[PDB]
Image (cartoon, rainbow, N blue to C red; front, side, top):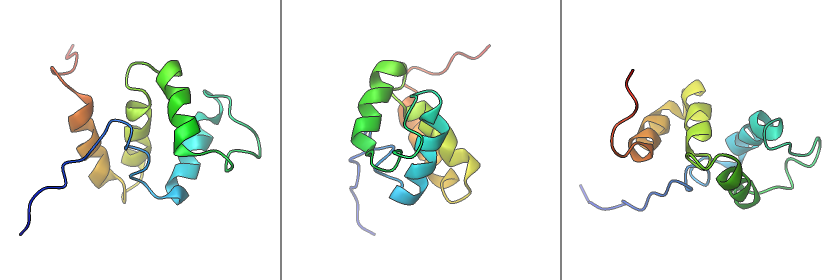
Length: 94
């Protein structure tokens, strides 16, 4: 077995998934980000990324996305992988 492949980024959380699933993410945020009604496809992980950066400076979308993956069984495997990166000094356990 080879090693490496440690090039993950809090932003890659989007590029990771296939455009297919991505479309859904934009829909769930359409309300928050206030995306278009029929022009949600013309957008790109980029334009959407920056939007989240300012909007949700907490995770910059990382979080909002992680969830979108949890709901899906084919993304749940990644959701857990993303979270690990999200947290830094442990969450706020209360």
